[PDB]
Image (cartoon, coloured by chain):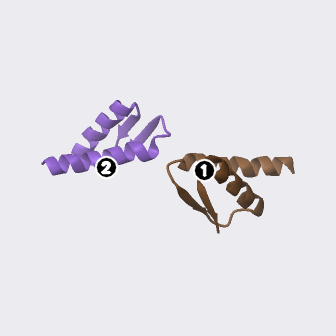
Chain colours: A purple, B brown
Amino acid sequence: GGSLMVTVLAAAVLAETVISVTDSILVLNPPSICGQMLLHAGEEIGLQVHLA
Amino acid sequence: GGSLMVTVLAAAVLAETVISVTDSILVLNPPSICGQMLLHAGEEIGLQVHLA
């Protein structure tokens, strides 16, 4: 489980960083864990992340 | 001519900025003016620009 979460957050931080510059982004069909962690990362970095 | 140069530099600055993060990039078949101005922009921003 820990490996899964750290993988999800590696992907999420990659998405937030490679783009950060933007004020809002959309992520399509991410894993549910990935969706939650992407929302958390967007909140922390102040980037409006939408989940589809 | 001035419009051409400013257009070329708008494109070059876009290329340098949207990517800046990278240490080296490659630009394929740019206009000769665009090639020279891309080299100038890379020198100013410290990004190793290659022209093909």
Residue at x 56% of width, y 59% of height: B25
Disc number at residue B46?
1
Q: Which residue is mark 2?
A: A11
**For the residues carrying marks 1 and 2, which lies nearer the camera in this image?**
1
Residue at x 59% of width, y 58% of height: B48
- Relative depth, front residue between A24 and A9: A9
Q: Quadrant of the C terminus of chain B?
A: bottom right
Residue at x 33% of width, y 31% of height: A44
Relative horizontal placement of residue B52, taking residue A38 as reference (left or right): right
Disc number at residue A22?
none
Residue at x 63% of width, y 66% of height: B28
Chain at tag 1 = B
Relative horizontal placement of residue B12, taking residue A45 as reference (left or right): right
Amino acid identity at mark 2? Ala
Residue lying at the far right in this picture: please name it: B1
Chain at tag 2 = A
Secondary structure at badge 2 equals helix
Q: Are marks 1 and 2 on the same chain?
A: no
